[PDB]
Amino acid sequence: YNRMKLMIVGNTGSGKTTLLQQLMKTKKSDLGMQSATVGIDVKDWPIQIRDKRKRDLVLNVWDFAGREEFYSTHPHFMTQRALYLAVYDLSKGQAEVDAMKPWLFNIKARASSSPVILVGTHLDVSDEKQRKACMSKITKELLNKRGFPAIRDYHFVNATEESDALAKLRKTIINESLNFKIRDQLVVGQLIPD
Ligand SMILES: Nc1nc2c(ncn2[C@@H]2O[C@H](COP(=O)(O)OP(=O)(O)O)[C@@H](O)[C@H]2O)c(=O)[nH]1
C-alpha cells in the first residue's frame, strides 16, 4: 500500500487551481482565468518513481478551497500521515506570510505532521523586491518557528509553466513522501487487509 496524503492549502487568490492542473499535466489552449474551489475535494497523483527497478507512489491530494468556510470549520482534515504544501502568493511580498500565519489554527491545534514546502506562485507578476521580502519574512517567521514545526523549505514557482518551476516540487514532495514514517512505519508501502 504505497499511498500517502497531501494537503494543498492557501488563501484564495494564491493560484492553487493552475498549479495543480499544470502538475497533473494539463497544458495550453485552455482557460487561463481558472475558477476557485469550494469544498474540500481529493484526487489521485500516481507519480512514477525510478531506480534500477521501477517503483511508484500515489498520493491522496486534498484540494482545499482558500476560503474560511472550508478551513476554520473543518479541523478534521489534519493528519500525521500527510504532507503539507502551502500555496503562497509572491505578488503581495511579505504580506502574504502574515496572511498565511493564522493557518496554525488547524495545523497546530490538531496534531499534524510533516509540512514540507511553500510554493511561491505569481512569480511571473511579482517583483524581485517582493520575492526577497517574501523569503526574508518566510524565513524570519515560519522557517524559524511558526509556532509548530513549520521549519522546512520553499520554492518560488512560475506555476503557470512546468519546466523546473514544477519539476522541483514534484521531486521535493515525492522524496519526502517516499521516506516518511509514522510510528516508524513507512507510510508509502504498508501491509493492509483489503
Ligand atoms: N499570472 C499567474 N496567474 C496564476 C498563477 N497561478 C494561478 N493563477 C491565477 O489563479 C486563479 C484561480 O484562483 P485560486 O486561488 O486557484 O482559487 P482557490 O482554489 O480558492 O485557491 C486563476 O484565475 C489565475 O488567474 C501564477 O502563478 N501566475
Image (tube, grey):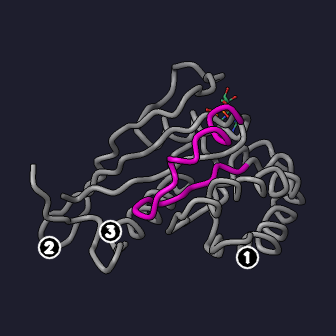
- The amino acid sitting under disc 3 is Leu
Residue 189 location, quadrant: bottom left
Q: Secondary structure at mark 2?
A: loop
Of residues 76 and 118, which is closer to you in this image?
Answer: 76
Q: Earlier in the sequence, mark 1 or mark 2?
A: 2
Would you say the beta carbon of the disc 1 residue lies within 8 angstroms of ligand 1? no
* Cα distance between the residues tagged 2 and 3: 16 Å
- The amino acid sitting under disc 1 is Lys
Which residue in the protein does label 1 denote? 145
Please provide percent x and percent y for residue 79.
46, 58
Q: Nearer the viewer, mark 3 or mark 1?
A: 1
Which residue in the protein does label 2 denote? 52
Magenta span covers which residues?
68-88
The reply to whether the magenta stretch includes residue 34 is no
Ligand 1 quadrant in view: top right
Horizontal relation, residue 31 to residue 131: left or right:
left
Q: Nearer the viewer, mark 1 or mark 2?
A: 1
Instruction: Look at 39% across and 69% down and name the residue there.
Output: 175
Which residue in the protein does label 3 denote? 178
* Cα distance between the residues tagged 3 and 1: 25 Å
* Cα distance between the residues tagged 1 and 2: 39 Å
